[PDB]
Length: 296
Length: 294
Ligand SMILES: *C(=O)[C@H](C[C@@H]1CCNC1=O)NC(=O)[C@H](CC1CCCCC1)NC(=O)c1cc2ccccc2[nH]1
Ligand SMILES: *C(=O)[C@H](C[C@@H]1CCNC1=O)NC(=O)[C@H](CC1CCCCC1)NC(=O)c1cc2ccccc2[nH]1
Image (cartoon, rainbow over all chains, first blue to last red; front, side):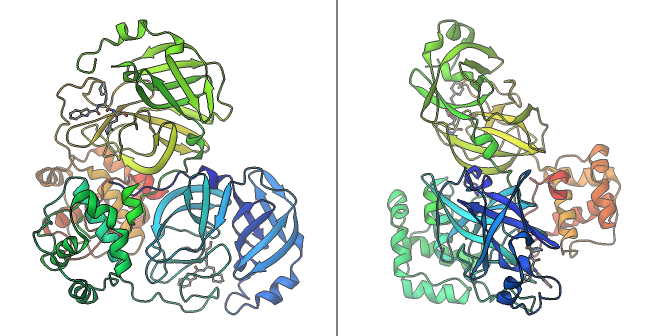
């Protein structure tokens, strides 16, 4: 069991470089529109309290240099949607995949294609934390990189990168420019909320462990949802909702370990620790695989 | 800090499906050649005579499909443990590529594929015992490992089999196995593995370059004394080449290699006492000095 990213070729073909004055970052080219963070129109002067409408009315089409590899794309229109800028260009991307813009929920995973200067550099799997940040790996110029899932030839874009918080975790928007989490595109003091562990993902990961031959943590017991939730609250774990139990249904049946039976295992893991042992290859309870991620 | 794979698009455009008899696996289509594991021609698995198995095949016994398109095989030959199927059509999306043979400790991306269609991408390392700790299911054979550098894809691994311990064995793209393995279903066992010491040190440098110094100390060590200690924890010996390779990261952080060796010695002695390094509760050994810089 390894953390696995989706194959990224369909998205690589959509990445372009956007330059506005002094700032260069990445854009997502789909049909005849390039999408990118609206903060690309900020200078050092504006970054602390921008008036994005004002700054945008100032700009004209030729203020944006869009580069698809060696080819410059001519901007013929510009617009803002929430915190994303939409640059209408000369030419529709001839490799636009089947795609959707989707908004994901905390606890869900996606692949990140990290890009610099419009050129894809690396790909890795992320989870939307319960505090709406991303534990990413993003350097200067990574803004505009996207997160996505693929479902049978259809790419669902869910994330575009905007910022790094002082703790080193990351914040961005969906592709309609709506931020994940209580963050703003302003150079002001911002902090992530206290994070919590994604309980249903930990359980799915334990089921993944049983499937792969590590069963030392299983026991004979079972808990209640109410009793397990008091434990989860003590250890900063997301409450296990009744719907969470249902999505684990397939894994309980394949292994014969009922969810509250596996919760009894997790309950004890939260106190005995691992007693010097390892679960999959990890000395920590891993919470960035969804039930779907384990089954696939 | 993440285990990052290379973008897989250039390799996705090369994956095809090869069927021989009742067996389907993946092939790598570059120009007018499809490369795949020669054991696609087995029915036979304990003591195959591949020379005899192959002379009985004709071109039409190999069904090659690139997506919906069937590729006509016009010839075939065997190069060590890989089959080279000459096809009627050159891959129009062949990238700039090379075939490279890697040494233990080297990392690469794996594009896991099934029925010629890519399924996922992840980072991997060649273990000191010439296995890889992959994630491969039935039908993954022919999946390839690669690095990409300046739009040039360097293919270094093709998947052949799973050992009884659950680790994986395969060949370079000229069909020479990594390690003492053969394409037979006989009893073969990965030798005892070790931790890639040079990679653990690179990663501790990465920890320093980011924010963390809590594991440093005031000691140094000789290279010989470090190796005498580290081998008691099943670490690979550190060589002068490894010390040289770490020079750039040493000079960038101000921490002499042997001073970082002293810190590693103490980390092995003490554990991390409830802390993490980068993101991990264990000493990570699948990042190379090169991976850290990039
Ligand atoms: C876009 O490419 C970068 C990506 C950052 C750079 C470093 N690591 C990343 O992920 N985005 C930024 O640099 C933003 C730009 C701002 C423009 C105006 C609106 C808000 C975003 N800045 C930051 O991410 C930033 C500034 C800052 C200051 C002090 C501590 C942390 C910190 N992070
Ligand atoms: C190719 O697709 C598969 C990949 C395997 C399947 C499961 N996980 C993998 O990586 N390759 C095989 O199944 C090989 C078949 C050839 C191997 C040698 C030459 C002829 C056939 N077999 C194994 O990987 C295998 C069989 C086996 C039996 C008992 C213990 C371990 C074991 N591994």
